[PDB]
Length: 129
Image (tube, rainbow, N blue to C red; front, side, top):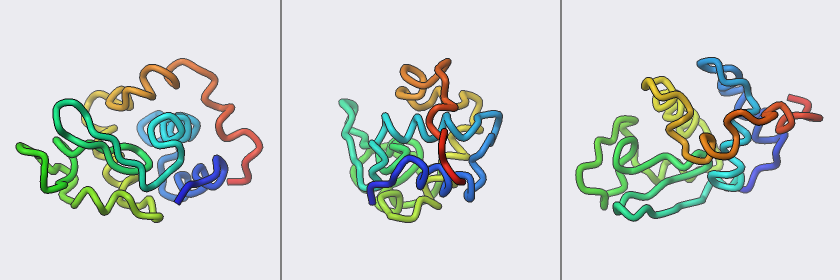
């Protein structure tokens, strides 16, 4: 499913990401935009051979098992395909584990380079959450 800005924001707030660990909701929407383009089916392979899955582009070497990433830690204990679902619950739950591991949202290269230190508020402006 390809979400709309406000639609994804509402779904994320309902899932308790709103200001989760200090990151206001705008950070999460901004990240989803540049990571997957609001598309739940997005997949992108990395040079090291791992692949990023879903709306939040969760990585296969650490968080999920995709059956083809040698040494996958699978910390979220879930098959990577579970993250391509129209229901963002598993992505959101796994994301809360990543964001809590000490590095914050810096784990997401796109947040780091395109959202960090920007008016993230603009991403949920006009939304009825």
